[PDB]
Each structure stands twice: as C-alpha cells, then as structure tokens.
Length: 188
Length: 188
Image (cartoon, rainbow over all chains, first blue to last red; front, side, top):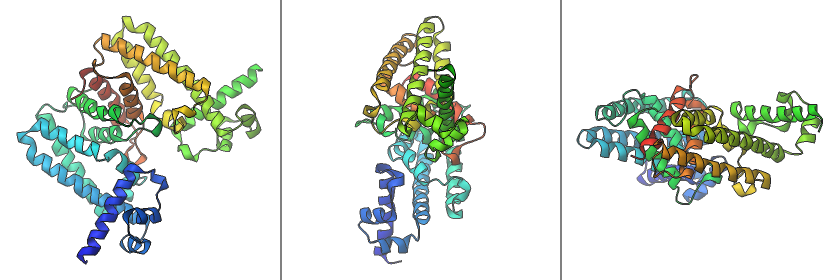
C-alpha cells in the first residue's frame, strides 16, 4: 500500500475516533465522516466498504493502542506501582474508553470479526496480569475480579448525559480518583 | 378524579418506569406503552396528551419517590448512619436511577416543566443535607462535593451496554460497593 494511502487510512480512523468522543453517535454518516476527515466519499469507501468495516477498523486500531499501553504498564509496573497504575487508568479515562466502547461495540462481542476478537482476548489476558500486579502492590483489593474492574472502568468513564455535563467536567474527572480509591480499599 | 381513573393513571406511570428499565428507550411508542399497561390508547392519551407529558409525569412521580427516600434517610440517619447511608444508595441503585435519568432527562434541565423543576431543586437541597450528614459520620470524605456525588451515583448506576451485561450483574452490583468505599476514603 502506498505510504500516502496508508496515512490517509490512518487519518480517517483517528478522525472517526475523535468524532465518537465529540459527536452524537447516531448523528454520524459515512458522508459526515468523509467530510470531517477532509477526504472524498469514494476514498473513504475504498478503504472501508461499509460502516461496520470502518467501525471494526477503529476497534482494531484502539485494541492495538490499548495493548501497547498495557505492555508499557506491565513492564514499568514493578518499579513504580502507584505511578504506573494511576497513569494507566487516567489515560484510558481521559482518552474516552467510556465513549468509544459504546460507540463501537456490537450487541454481542461474538459479532466482532476474528482479528478483533483475538485482540479482545489479548486485552483481557493483559488486564488480569495488570490487576494481579496491582493486587500484589496493595493497589486493588484481592477480592475484586478483573472483569469487575474492566466493566467498572468502562462504566465510570462514560461521560454524563448532556443535562448533567459541566464545562470543567470536574464532577466526572473526580469519579476516576474515587473508583481507584474504591478498588484499593475494596467494597463497603 | 374518580378513584379508578386515578389508579389507572398511576399504573400507566409505573408500567412506563418499569419499561424504561427493561426495554430499549428508543423502541417505546405510546401504543407500546398502552399495550403493556393493559389500557387503550385513548385512555392513555386522555391522561397524557403526548410523550413529553407522560415522561414528565414519570419524572414528577420519581422525584416525589426520591424525596420520600431522602426524608426517611435524613430523619433516620443520626441513629444508624452507615446502615441508612448504605440502604439509601443501594435502593436508588437497585431501582434504576441509572436507567431512568437518561430515559427521562431532556437535553437541558431548563426544559423541565416548573413543577418538576421545583422537585429537582428540593432533591438537590436534600442531597446536600444527606451528604453533610454522611461527612459528619465519616462516611463521605469532606472534599467531595454533593454534585460530584450525584453525578457519580447516576453514572455508576447506568447499566452496561448489552455486550458487557451478565445474568447475575455481579460486576455491575459490585460497582456500588466500590463507589461508596471511594467516597469514604476520598480520591486516590
């Protein structure tokens, strides 16, 4: 693939991920995405034959990015547990885990294409490794399951409905600090 | 209003609140609601002239219920702080605060009719009273604002997207325990 075609494809993907964080998910059309990416509809469609394909290419890209954050965190963890644990969660939270998952998840995780499903499995495996490190270093209570942590992180990261949103987002940003505190001290 | 007309109106409201907890919010029509409530469309519409009116009547009912839970909790708090604090939050969580708010909130809280807006104000005032009691009894860290607590509670109560939902909902139910723990120990 020509270098410029590959850069253009990557830009369409990045643009789409950003749109999912700033725009109503149901308001976006292929035409809208092409326009925001600064490419023609035909260029968009040659890369991604349909909406599902574009959305799955976005999933694939995001899983690849999450895996690199997990691998950085796993390798760095032993010599800065609290620092790595905190920065890892801050990064997923601030980068929209909570907008991107609902934007891109199909009704069943079984509908993910096989390459994406493989990435999901690696992500779940790395999460267990990370949680086990966190438990080792007293950062996450031992009774908390890895799946509970994941679902919780996705849940607390979902931005509030418009009516409850603030310009600072302080109420929302504070929720991450409280979730990590809860994970550490365990359930009340 | 005849006793039987008033009971019928209350049943349409309860049915609608339950549907919002079990059904896709965008999938519901006035016709669907009338059918699930066991009433005719014309009976439904004489009570509630349009969807907004029905949804606002539901909001009004729910705010009235939340206010009674707040008043029970405020009066009972001093002689069982942890017990009252926990049961109050368990009850809003288990009764779908997290499904009902997004189902019923308009884009701006300014769009609430005046009787509903008054109920919202009383609810916010009672929440401050409750939080101040909780802080007094060491259940909520003193730095946490009442609005942060509300937004957090609404956020953690929002059920997960289908793909991440489990039959037990244990991952989800555990999130409440972790949120209260975080509130108590304060931010990490």
